[PDB]
Picture (cartoon, rainbow, N blue to C red):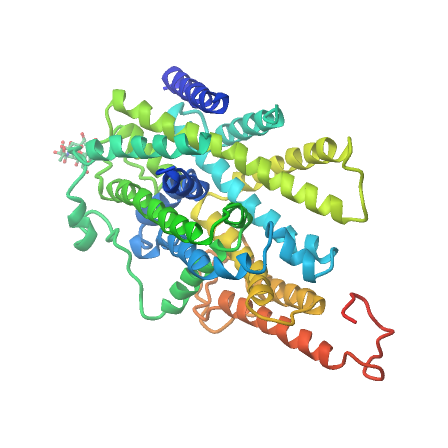
Length: 493
Ligand SMILES: *[C@@H]1O[C@H](CO)[C@@H](O[C@@H]2O[C@H](CO)[C@@H](O[C@@H]3O[C@H](CO)[C@@H](O)[C@H](O)[C@@H]3O)[C@H](O)[C@H]2NC(C)=O)[C@H](O)[C@H]1NC(C)=O
């Protein structure tokens, strides 16, 4: 349990770093590597445990595996539409549009939500690696996450003195070497049978009532429109010189997302359909014990033979550990650099980068660990990340680039309106009891009060409308008399 897991993880991390430096030492092909790396930005750590939750958990099923189909569609929406109206106007990074119209100050107030979103994502990755380690070396839930994240952040500490391709290859080989074998286990029954007929559990094929179809469309639109905005995607496409190449790149990344989601769904489906009274895990099921998180590492380690298991499971753990470094470094660096330049001015010569990035990266890792420690879901963290991004960033991104005449008053008005309409409406994974109680709430765990009336999409739309309304109203009273131009907090005249 302990020794085999530790040696497997160490060996595979050594081998992945070795291949990385083999690359870093030293056409007809350029569609391959770019598409694979840009889909490697999303896939990895996230999907496998997230969609494992989505499929395995009773009641939700496939029809509630929103993100594994949500993001791919998100990629197409980002490319097929926003590929054009940023090339022609010309922009270097997504930092630029906000700091071009909204002065310079407004940008940091806008990009704090991006920090919190990628903080959610980093917490999800840390939770996934904690579960994988807690299965491979079978220690604990508190111990695995803290050990994992401390090592990850202290390695990213001196990580400053391509590898994203080998991540996907390891992920693909690891899943596609276990599932053909686990599906053969006598403990498992026909994956088709429990899909439609519900022999040993509710059908792992998701079921949605006509009543909460509004909530289903809320979640779908949230994920689909909250994937586009984020920084890594814009940074990648903007660094691509030719436009059509970006469209084919979006096609290929969405296809990579969808193909890598195929082995991940079947893993959770087997985990659900399996008769657990035969395996050596004990009759207490992953739901009847508060450990539904670990369903994928559990099905790999226990429902596969000893020799096959460590290849795939160590590959998964090593890949997600590697992704942790990139996510942590990028998330801390962008905030520190942008907002520190923002505040009044600060010498970047020989203090800012090292000192500020150090402080921010350490505290960011600590906070990601702290919130990944209490939430026993990863699908929930995803939802929360894309949820906040959808609430705040996307409306103003869409009005800045697709709409004309947007101004700085609209930025603050949309910010306040969106944030209020979201936080006041309640959040069910944490204990955010709502204050409004939109028609359609159902009694639950007193932490979960879902309103079938979509308020997330309503908040997004009304924040965009608030931006437009206050912007053009202030533009209309631009004048003397009508709050004369003497009164001017953020410049528009
Ligand atoms: C899986 O579940 C089954 C049943 O849900 C468990 O198997 C049963 O275990 C008992 C205890 O050894 C076996 O003895 C039986 O006990 C009852 C108690 O009332 C008695 O009336 C019977 O005459 C008999 O002595 C029982 O035969 C056995 N049933 C079967 C079908 O094997 C089992 O412990 C669970 N876990 C596994 C199989 O890992």
